[PDB]
């Protein structure tokens, strides 16, 4: 069954582009990464950096997750990210999203050995 680490890459990593290139980026990515299979995931962030740079966040600034957990880490540097948010016209199975480009610090939750990201918590 898919591991938590593999699930993080599938839902959040897009090293193949430096940023979202059109307003349809989220619509395409959400569907292809299988994030709209059972329902429309309401919000999802993609990170446009190398996997190694994102995995490195687990050894950066330790911070509390939004939920209180203390296995969260924030990147020392800003990263290129795309914020995908469901629109008013979104209706399963035709999930629709608004694409927003941004450069922010990311906060992820890390677990395992090797200690890698398993959940995207927020961008600040």
Image (cartoon, grey):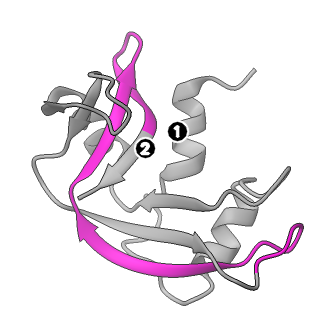
Relative vertical location of residue 45 with respect to residue 94 in this rendering, above or below: above
Relative vertical location of residue 43 with respect to residue 85 in this rendering, above or below: above
State the image coordinates of residue 29 (x, y, percent, origin top left): 64, 67
Would you identify the image quadrant in which residue 110 lies?
top left
Identify the disc placed on residue 21. none
User: What secondary structure is the stretch in magenta mostly built from?
Assistant: strand
Residue that appears at 65% across and 80% down: 87
Q: Which residue is mark 2?
A: 120
Residue that appears at 75% across and 64% down: 31
114 drawn magenta: yes
17 drawn magenta: no
Tell me whether the residue at label 1 lies in contact with that at label 2, contact meaning CB atoms closer than 8 angstroms. Answer: yes
> Farthest residue toward the right?
93
Q: Which residue is mark 1?
A: 8
User: How far apart are the two marked residues, 1 and 2, measured between alpha carbons?
Assistant: 8 Å
State the image coordinates of residue 6 (x, y, percent, origin top left): 58, 32
Residue that appears at 50% across and 51% down: 12
Would you identify the image quadrant in which residue 27 lies?
bottom right
Q: Quadrant of the N terminus?
A: top right
Find the magenta span and give its range: 90-119
Side of 76 relative to 8 (left or right): left
Relative vertical location of residue 90 with respect to residue 58 in this rendering, above or below: below
Q: Quadrant of the C terminus?
A: bottom left
Side of 86 relative to 40 (left or right): left
Q: SS of the residue at dot 1?
A: helix
Q: SS of the residue at dot 2?
A: strand
Q: How many marks?
A: 2
CA neighbours of label 1 inside 10 A, class few (<14), some (14 to 19), many (20+):
some
């Amino acid at each position: 069954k898919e591991t938590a680490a593999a699930k993080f890459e599938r839902q959040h990593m897009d090293s193949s582009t430096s940023a979202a290139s059109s307003s349809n980026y989220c619509n395409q990515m959400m569907k292809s990464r299988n994030l709209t299979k059972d329902r429309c995931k309401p919000v999802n962030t993609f990170v446009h950096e190398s996997l190694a740079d994102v995995q490195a966040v687990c050894s950066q600034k330790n911070v509390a997750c939004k939920n209180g957990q203390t296995n969260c880490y924030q990147s020392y540097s800003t990263m290129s990210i795309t914020d995908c948010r469901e629109t008013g016209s979104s209706k399963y199975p035709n999930c629709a999203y608004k694409t927003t480009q941004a450069n922010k610090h990311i906060i992820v939750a890390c677990e395992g050995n090797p200690y890698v990201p398993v959940h995207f918590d927020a961008s600040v």
